[PDB]
View 1 (cartoon, rainbow, N blue to C red):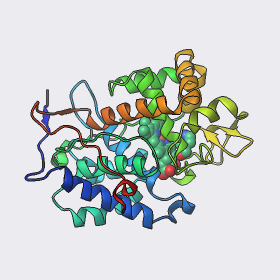
View 2 (spheres, protein in one colour):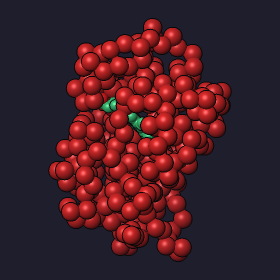
View 3 (cartoon, rainbow, N blue to C red):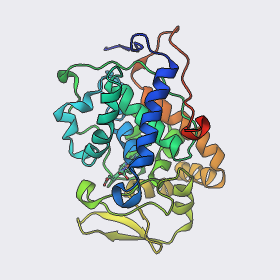
Length: 292
Ligand code: HEM
Ligand SMILES: OCc1ccncc1
């Protein structure tokens, strides 16, 4: 039973990681034309989730710790199609700060993106350590989109996530868009797709959804407003337990933000043992808070 102990990059402290945050945030501000003016925020969130979502609680394989997305087996996972854009965005940041581990950089990209998109503060811990190519998880550990609530619940239990955590994490589907060439799905989840809000839940409950087969022959739920939901998204209003939580978050964005922050930190930390004397989690200032 593999143990991965967090080990702080030698000699580095909060201020050093705040500089990496700031470089990511400045580049997010600059590269505003990407994906028809969405910017890189959403793809960075998806990247941080996909490098973490390979985790298996039963044997501690996968997860964010080892930075294994840098190896071709994982980079070329069909489930990761499109994430190469996020990797390429982070390359100049890694060149400026070569001392940071790959797992720390990929996870920090997601935290930075959420915060810079006016989302909640997400506490973040350093100390992921790059592991060798033979520790890369096989493809097939990330979730299918064509499934129902039972599939979603079973899937997320492999990551030690419960119903509230699942529903909170899925709120990230307000961000960005699906792209037919990446995943065989097409369209945004709502209007505000580069500002972090509770729109996903509001749209699930309030839109007029029609089940359609898209140009890749996959089923998705499409609204009159030009929004879409995957079958796994729509399952959150089919399952009674999930539906109750969707209503809670549609009614209270502050609660969503609190629950998302916890769930996303947990996701990004799964598999990692933090020594009892490790630094406390860092809460990075936004560029705005620093006057930058
Ligand atoms: C059942 C679980 C999930 C399924 C089946 C799923 C599936 C998908 C699919 C098919 C796409 C479109 C990819 C593309 O065409 O570019 C997507 C996008 C996205 N996913 Fe999820 N997802 C899941 C959970 C999550 C979680 C837990 C998060 C983060 C907390 C997340 C964040 C995102 C973001 C931000 C996008 C937009 C990316 C972009 O605009 O480039 N997803 N997801
Ligand atoms: O990226 C927007 C989106 C919308 C619905 N499901 C997944 C992703």
